[PDB]
Amino acid sequence: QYWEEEIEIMSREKLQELQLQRLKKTINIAANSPYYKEVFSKNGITGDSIQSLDDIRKIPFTTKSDMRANYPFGLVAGDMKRDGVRIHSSTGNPTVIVHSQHDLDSWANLVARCLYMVGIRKTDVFQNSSGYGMFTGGLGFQYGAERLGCLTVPAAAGNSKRQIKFISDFKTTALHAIPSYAIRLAEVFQEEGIDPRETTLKTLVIGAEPHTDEQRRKIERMLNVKAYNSFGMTEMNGPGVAFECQEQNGMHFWEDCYLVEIIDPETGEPVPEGEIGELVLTTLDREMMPLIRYRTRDLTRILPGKCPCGRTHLRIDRIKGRSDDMFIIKGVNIFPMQVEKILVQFPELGSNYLITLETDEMIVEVELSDLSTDNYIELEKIRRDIIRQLKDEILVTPKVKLVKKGSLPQSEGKAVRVKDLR
Amino acid sequence: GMSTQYWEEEIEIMSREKLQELQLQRLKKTINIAANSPYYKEVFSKNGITGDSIQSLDDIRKIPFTTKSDMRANYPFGLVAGDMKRDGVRIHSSSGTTGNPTVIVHSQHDLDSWANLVARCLYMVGIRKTDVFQNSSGYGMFTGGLGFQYGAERLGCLTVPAAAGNSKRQIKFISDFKTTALHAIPSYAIRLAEVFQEEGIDPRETTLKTLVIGAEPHTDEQRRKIERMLNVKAYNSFGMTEMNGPGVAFECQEQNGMHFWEDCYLVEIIDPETGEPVPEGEIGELVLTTLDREMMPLIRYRTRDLTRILPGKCPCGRTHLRIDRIKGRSDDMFIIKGVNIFPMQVEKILVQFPELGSNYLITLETVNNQDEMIVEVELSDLSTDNYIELEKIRRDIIRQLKDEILVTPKVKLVKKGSLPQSEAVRVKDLRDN
Ligand SMILES: Nc1ncnc2c1ncn2[C@@H]1O[C@H](COP(=O)(O)OP(=O)(O)O)[C@@H](O)[C@H]1O
Ligand SMILES: Nc1ncnc2c1ncn2[C@@H]1O[C@H](COP(=O)(O)OP(=O)(O)O)[C@@H](O)[C@H]1O
Ligand SMILES: [K+]
Ligand SMILES: [K+]
Ligand SMILES: [K+]
Ligand SMILES: [Zn+2]
Ligand SMILES: [Zn+2]
């Protein structure tokens, strides 16, 4: 079942002419913003420059530095005073995105499309544990779930006792939470004397944080739910950008509203088909403030072949991480997902871990699991196996410490996996 | 007024005669809808309320009042009249886990009616689509959040969903986005004027032109202080979750009484003792009936709010009745930082800690134009806990109170017998009100 079958299963040929029509429209609109008027002027970008989807490569990339330099409204193309109805924001000077009613409705429709794809219906009780206000996850899932017709529960962030009360009393069936907060809720259910596997919950929507497939499976087993990967960023509206189908194998990118490129961070050229590179995105249905070839700093790849769900829209792999998550120790580049890929395979460990960098030495603290009935000798042998598998993957020997369950701190938002004290 | 502009002129200046037949039509419809809920089906059954009981607006007095106690007893969905699974799109819940909260269930119709009322309110005080509207109200379950958000987008304003706190970020949004309309509780509007001068900005030389202030009692003088500090026009905004949230009653540009939208609400002023209508223009309890709500309508709901109907025609030309300021309540509820709290919510948290005594005192004070809530509770001599352990318990008390009442109080562990007795435990409100 599809929210918009004509688009979701649209032929690649028809998708291409839709992308080209909307790419030309986006460029004509964006030409009215002070920023893209100047960019187009200096690079000879006119109304005749785009004749094919490949002609987008004539236009230079938009970086986060360019957006900071033109903060707050240098990239606003429309009439903000008359048609601008919302401002959202993403250390530093946060960037803002300005939306028109058109832009909000397009965003809401994409979120309803995503929720419907993973089996959520108007009969579902949808609870949003994302922060509201300026955070796109709040109003983003709120409008999308109301668009679909769910009985929504705008719980917002924190207060786990109240979250559990709403789930129990309102019979919540669909929940939006960051993966680490979903684990925290399952723990508070047990603390309050409720079996986290015997609630009314059926579907979880998890995003914002990089996480392994096994981290998601741990969440699924903990709460007896089906959990789906949700991709988004403020620059691209917020949620509803890319989402897993019921196949749970790659996130379908809505190519009617986004032009996806996977560029080599060194050369600035497209990577060979299916290789890892920087995700570079162009809005195709945004009017107040469109973004052209925006360098997301997110590393991923395009998963090949058509998906068994019948949707023609391309699938991206699990986000490897963001460029700013990468840390260097002893001249060697390491991503925290490399450390998680190893830790999740050990069932004696918990889901909370912390990487500390000191003067260079790398410390990997990871909480012990409650299920563990292991003694010192057997747990110390497991700790030795971890230092070893970490030395083989990250190519540096870290210090590994098995810590008490609950000893590591829990973040208000996205969990902080790296503490650089150098 | 000839130069006066209306969001919905046909409704806003509608004759009292035409308003009466609109209220009667919608009152009959509300009663027929509410009869489908388990709660009103029972109430109507015991009191012989049928489809022929309401022939005039005065016939509403045949129906008994709906109290908060009744609602908590029918928690969560005893008063839901519509098809919640198919048409229910939102739940607004009051605070707490120590008792049954209040739940208001809305359909898309109910949200659109509520958004239209908020747009009507904002337009009345001169806000247009050309304005930059910043909402400093909390979002999530708080109706001021999503209420003004939908209302301001309906009007077409460039909205800034700032949400509560972080005054330096509030001032940054006002300066960088050129905010012209701001929704804030009166004490927070003063705080932002103070933070503006702390950061070296003249609070009178910003892009701000209009302020919408509500959630708590404030005097006309406290509003004038706000207008002088920020060089703005500030307007009183009334609402309650039960009645949607914001958009229920609002001042016009005359700044003399809050216009109640009688097309969506039937207003009664009742004696808190007798339950009978008060003499025209006297102070009494505000008893309200929804007239445009379908998923969960409320009939003759005892709000516990005390006010009076201001007499005479308004020069703005609107025919909808005006209520005076809400100065207080007939119940034991208190409001601090615009958040509603019952003393029982505090007591039900404290009793869980065996290191504490039974004697406690809630003090409400104003410190540098900001409100503070102090919870003093006596130590039990039964505890064998040292300083470090007690202080850890005091932090756990603050934490559990914060989660419960949705405001962070100051908690002080006092000596056994230090707090005075007389008796229900009192709320010492030392604020200028
Ligand atoms: N499902 C996901 N998996 C991994 N990383 C994600 C996922 N969703 C979002 N992200 C990360 O979060 C970034 C977007 O964050 P941002 O828009 O600022 O905040 P928000 O979390 O409030 O949507 C992405 O660029 C990416 O790095
Ligand atoms: N403008 C106002 N003046 C005085 N009291 C007000 C005003 N607006 C709201 N209130 C009080 O707040 C109550 C409604 O509180 P509630 O909806 O629970 O919280 P909130 O609107 O602050 O989220 C009203 O019944 C009334 O007592
Ligand atoms: K529904
Ligand atoms: K606008
Ligand atoms: K209030
Ligand atoms: Zn698929
Ligand atoms: Zn008036």
Image (spheres, coloured by chain):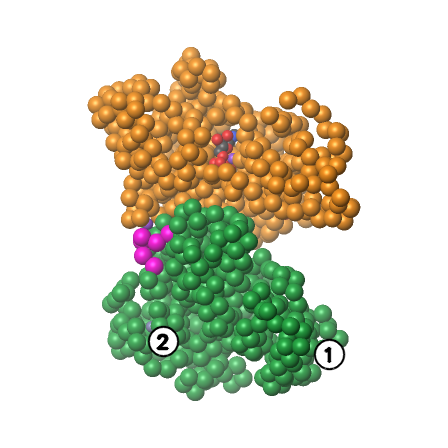
Chain colours: A green, B orange
The x, y position of residue B328, in whole percent, is 54, 25
Front residue (pair B351, A371): A371
- Location of the N terminus of chain A by quadrant is bottom left
* Residue occupying image coordinates x 54% and y 84%: A266
Q: Could you tell me which chain the residue with mark 2 belongs to?
A: A
The x, y position of residue B341, in whole percent, is 55, 35
* Residue occupying image coordinates x 48% and y 53%: A194
Front residue (pair B187, B296): B296
The x, y position of residue B271, in whole percent, is 45, 16
Name the image quarter holding residue B431: top right
* Residue occupying image coordinates x 47% and y 32%: B238
Indicate left or right for A273 with A266 as reference: left
Front residue (pair B125, B320): B320
Amino acid type at mark 1: Asp
Indicate which disc residue A360 carries.
1
Q: Earlier in the sequence, mark 1 or mark 2?
A: 2
Mark 1 residue crowding within 10 angstroms, few (<14) / some (14–19) / many (20+):
few
* Dominant secondary structure (helix, strand or loop) of the stretch shown in magenta: loop
Residue indicated by mark 2 = A314
